[PDB]
Length: 49
Length: 49
Image (cartoon, rainbow over all chains, first blue to last red; front, side, top):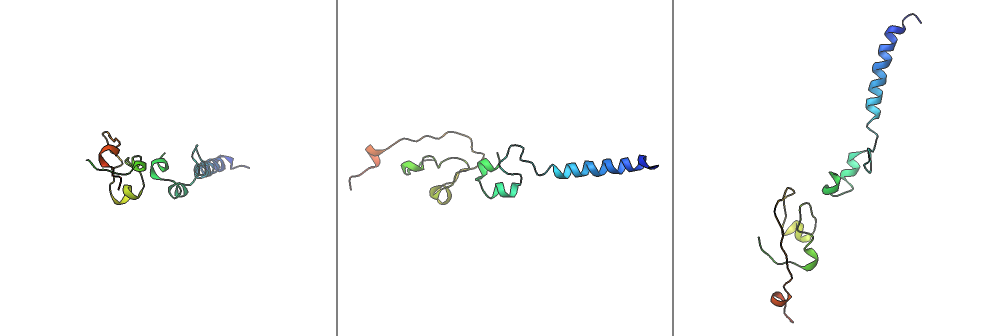
């Protein structure tokens, strides 16, 4: 437990990167969280919406 | 631009629209600006035969 100072930095960096990566699987109000499905399921005028 | 089409195809004349006439006859840019004018012509463009 002597090296908590250096472990905290690594933990913070890893956790921030993990949160950034996990933010990709969110709808944000859209129908689907993957844009490949959106582009292959609707016409452009609402695909862009 | 002037032409004559069917009654059900008046909706197809718009940016980002799909259809037989929309794809193979007349296509509008997605960034189209202007106005669209249409009127029925049974008294001029209709024949009993």
